[PDB]
Amino acid sequence: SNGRDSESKRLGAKSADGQTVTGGSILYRQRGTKIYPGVNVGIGGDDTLFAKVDGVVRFERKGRDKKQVSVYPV
Amino acid sequence: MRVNITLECTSCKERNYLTNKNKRNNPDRLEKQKYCPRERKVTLHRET
Amino acid sequence: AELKITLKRSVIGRPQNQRATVKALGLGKVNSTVTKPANEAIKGMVNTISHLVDVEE
Amino acid sequence: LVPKRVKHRREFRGKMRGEAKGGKEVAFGEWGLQATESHWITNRQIEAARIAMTRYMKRGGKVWIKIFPHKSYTSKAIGVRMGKGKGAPEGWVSPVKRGKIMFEIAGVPEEVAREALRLASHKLPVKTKIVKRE
RNA sequence: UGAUGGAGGUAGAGCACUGUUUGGACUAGGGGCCCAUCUCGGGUUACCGAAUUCAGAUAAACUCCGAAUGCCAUUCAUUUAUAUCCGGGAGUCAGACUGCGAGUGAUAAGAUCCGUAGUCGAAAGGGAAACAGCCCAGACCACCAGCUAAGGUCCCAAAAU
RNA sequence: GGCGGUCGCCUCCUAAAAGGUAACGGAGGCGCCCAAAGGUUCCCUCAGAAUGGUUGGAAAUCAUUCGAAGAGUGUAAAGGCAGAAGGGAGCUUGACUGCGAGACCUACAAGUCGAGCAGGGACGAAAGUCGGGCUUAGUGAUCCGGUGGUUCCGCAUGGAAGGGCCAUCGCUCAACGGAUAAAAGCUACCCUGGGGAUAACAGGCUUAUCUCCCCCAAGAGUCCACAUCGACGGGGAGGUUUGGCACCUCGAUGUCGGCUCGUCGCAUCCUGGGGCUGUAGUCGGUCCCAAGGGUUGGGCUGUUCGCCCAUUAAAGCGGCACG
RNA sequence: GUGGUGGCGAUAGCGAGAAGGAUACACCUGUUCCCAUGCCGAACACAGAAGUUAAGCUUCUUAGCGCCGAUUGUAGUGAAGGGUUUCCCUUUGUGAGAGUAGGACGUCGCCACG
Ligand SMILES: [K+]
Ligand SMILES: [K+]
Ligand SMILES: [K+]
Ligand SMILES: [K+]
Ligand SMILES: [K+]
Ligand SMILES: [K+]
Ligand SMILES: [K+]
Ligand SMILES: [K+]
Ligand SMILES: [K+]
Ligand SMILES: [K+]
Ligand SMILES: [K+]
Ligand SMILES: [K+]
Ligand SMILES: [K+]
Ligand SMILES: [K+]
Ligand SMILES: [K+]
Ligand SMILES: [K+]
Ligand SMILES: [K+]
Ligand SMILES: [K+]
Ligand SMILES: [K+]
Ligand SMILES: [K+]
Ligand SMILES: [K+]
Ligand SMILES: [Mg+2]
Ligand SMILES: [Mg+2]
Ligand SMILES: [Mg+2]
Ligand SMILES: [Mg+2]
Ligand SMILES: [Mg+2]
Ligand SMILES: [Mg+2]
Ligand SMILES: [Mg+2]
Ligand SMILES: [Mg+2]
Ligand SMILES: [Mg+2]
Ligand SMILES: [Mg+2]
Ligand SMILES: [Mg+2]
Ligand SMILES: [Mg+2]
Ligand SMILES: [Mg+2]
Ligand SMILES: [Mg+2]
Ligand SMILES: [Mg+2]
Ligand SMILES: [Mg+2]
Ligand SMILES: [Mg+2]
Ligand SMILES: [Mg+2]
Ligand SMILES: [Mg+2]
Ligand SMILES: [Mg+2]
Ligand SMILES: [Mg+2]
Ligand SMILES: [Mg+2]
Ligand SMILES: [Mg+2]
Ligand SMILES: [Mg+2]
Ligand SMILES: [Zn+2]
């Protein structure tokens, strides 16, 4: 019989492009590297992308078919 | 039979670590070099 | 230059963004009028509720 | 007609909006029977139409069935209340949208083709029109 | 609301993957018959045909693609006037229908279950003969004054026989 | 309501391109595993196919070529990874201690990520990486107990007893936010509080089923689709059936059959009129019109129904809270 | 020109063909040396300069494949309505995928030897 489902995990983008964030702010929750960590951005043990410094978030292209998040301080 | 174990410090006898082992694959007591917070140094730790 | 906007249709039964647009423009009762600059922001608002308003230059 | 195997035993009924995605032109035969309304076509209906056509053609020429009943549908028996999970699969349907050519024929003179496709159309739950290949 | 920048794979579409599938060509291989039988090599039903290829379909749990919208954001712009936070006091945890998008159901139900907007609830007035939920519209009051909305204008019954 | 199913956690679809989102909706997994299948350093690239080749066979090992991933990634699925997260090897134990700016998630309790700082390390020449594993399941509050540690307390005082603090163990408390350390049934002998929030009767909505009526016409009918019948399929009407729903009624809407009294519909049983006939006649068949009237008494059974007996011009079918 | 080393979505690729080595880059010659092969100096490592451009590699030609891809039209769809309302239609904005005209056999740097 059916009738089961796991709790939803609230994945996806947590900070906006062009938004100023403090260091440590989570930018993107994901399974796998759907988006890659760019400049001043790290990737956690469960693929969460977080800011390493204070700066403005930019979602960028990584080559042809990949994306990327970076944080640029002012 | 995978079981939970404690790794005691062979120097000061502090039960410093919680870990687990498969007894079938590791019959003898697991021995590891682990940092002892009491002695503040890496010491031989053995399952007790 | 200027836009004279008059509320000609009721806001009852309309979505929230349209009621809030009417309020953002400063319109109240039906047939209430208001004069606004012909900015791109104001013209955008008129477009959102054009079915509810009449506008004059 | 029935698929030999299916990935999922049960499927949504779905929706039939718009004209058919593909198969709107006669592709293999000389004459086609075009659906002008959207409707589920059962495998029983496809078979009745097919036999009605071939027999009138007197085993002459070729017949192409351009639709397949990919989709299953379930039912609940009389006396069964609502709830307690989706019913067991009952039959197979092809969802057919207006403009889909359901059948094509070739190898027979036009007079026979027009009467062949007329007899088939009366077996289907959809209104139809004859279409000549271009 | 506008501008700008982003995330996201739905509608549609497509087949490049995975399932489902039609015809054609050709085919390893697969069925019986004879000659030859040590069952060893052939020749055939326009016998069944993998895979390949050509053409054509199909998909909630397929995707080479992919919107509209919605969403997040900006020391941004215009209009607008709310937002949070701290504390006192609650009530609410049976909802309904209508439109739209889905599931369940027989793409039955004034059915059921979500999403979304509205009205009812807790809203009188006008229209829909009557008719909570539809359409128009929100009653602080007075008037034997005027203009309109939906809907109307031969009589009941106001207004174009 | 019962029976069955379900109860916590993970992945997907549903879910409407942020997030979230229900149903006894559609599919699967979990209650672990690993001493490397962890860390690091260095190195490596797959599955298949074609061709050749002893045992050797479709397929075990070998060689070349082709091959962008069609493999693998312990374990479900999704997302990801071949600048590897896949594969091999050396050394290792960071599957470190104290923590932790800032975020995500969130009613709470919890859950998730985390740069960076210090202590002491592993690998590496160094850069640097390392606080387990491609990612997301593999779990359980408190109370009460066990064990280890402890510069804490010690009821006059020293001790002790007994506590505290830190670490860790004992949950299919799985009805998985766990009522108790400890618990199954019968009630037609029943009772109270409530509910049309919720069933049984009747109404209502629906019409799958049912009854009736049609479309197409392969066929049957010696020939001949359509006198009559009519496969495979298709479309309706009705609201008498079997059902679905739960909208009025549970501060009660009395339930089958019969009796009495009927009344209405017409999809007409008889009688009246008519067309076609595979209508000689007599009997009939079938369709059309027609609701004026008529439409039996018994045997059995509570029965309705039905079988039977004997009649009849006939002995119609339904509705009216199954009047 | 060649050899290093980078940025830019393959418009940078792939296949086919042609030319070149002065240097350079490679094949290449060896296992004494550090080091190496779950066997093999093939590789890795080291030492070397007889030969060769044959291959790689550079440059050049080709769009056959892959990649990029305007416009128009259409699907869908926001908003506002409508009907004969499981569907369909009008108005207004937006606008694909497909299929195509075409583009493209790269471009922008820095260093070294010429
Ligand atoms: K038809
Ligand atoms: K495909
Ligand atoms: K899809
Ligand atoms: K609704
Ligand atoms: K209101
Ligand atoms: K290792
Ligand atoms: K419980
Ligand atoms: K009793
Ligand atoms: K009906
Ligand atoms: K009828
Ligand atoms: K006849
Ligand atoms: K009652
Ligand atoms: K009666
Ligand atoms: K007659
Ligand atoms: K009568
Ligand atoms: K009797
Ligand atoms: K009796
Ligand atoms: K009753
Ligand atoms: K060498
Ligand atoms: K060469
Ligand atoms: K090219
Ligand atoms: Mg999920
Ligand atoms: Mg982890
Ligand atoms: Mg679609
Ligand atoms: Mg309802
Ligand atoms: Mg109320
Ligand atoms: Mg009212
Ligand atoms: Mg009332
Ligand atoms: Mg008048
Ligand atoms: Mg007139
Ligand atoms: Mg959405
Ligand atoms: Mg979402
Ligand atoms: Mg691994
Ligand atoms: Mg004392
Ligand atoms: Mg004492
Ligand atoms: Mg619970
Ligand atoms: Mg008794
Ligand atoms: Mg009582
Ligand atoms: Mg009551
Ligand atoms: Mg009720
Ligand atoms: Mg009643
Ligand atoms: Mg209800
Ligand atoms: Mg009463
Ligand atoms: Mg009649
Ligand atoms: Mg395009
Ligand atoms: Zn120690």
Image: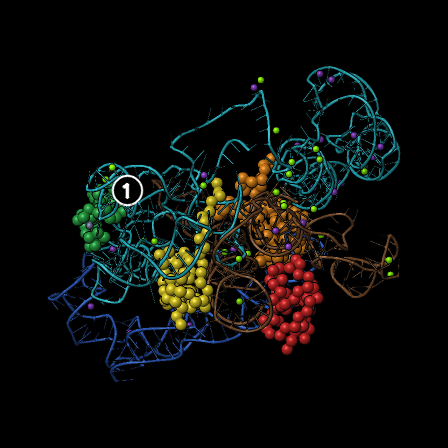
Chain colours: A yellow, B green, C red, D orange, E brown, F cyan, G blue
Which residue is located at x 66 percent, y 64 percent? C28
Which residue is located at x 40 percent, y 72 percent? A74
Mark 1 = which residue? B3
Give SS at disc 1.
Answer: strand
Query: Foreground: C1 or F287?
Result: C1
Is F319 left, or right, of D80 in this rendering? Answer: right
Q: Is residue D55 visible?
A: no
Q: Where is residue F180 drawn, in percent x and y?
A: 40, 34
Q: Is residue A16 visible?
A: yes
Q: Is residue D80 above or below residue E131?
A: above
**Number of dots carrying numbers:** 1
Q: What is the quadrant of residue A47 in the picture?
A: bottom left
Which residue is located at x 61 percent, y 48 percent? D41
Q: Where is residue F125 drawn, in percent x and y?
A: 20, 65
* Callout 1 crowding tier (Cα within 10 Å): few <14, some 14–19, many ≥20: few
Quarter of the figure that contains the C terminus of chain D: bottom right
Is F236 left, or right, of D31 in this rendering? Answer: right
Is F23 left, or right, of G28 in this rendering? Answer: right
Q: Chain of mark 1?
A: B
Q: Is residue F246 above or below residue A31?
A: above
Type of the residue with mark 1: Val
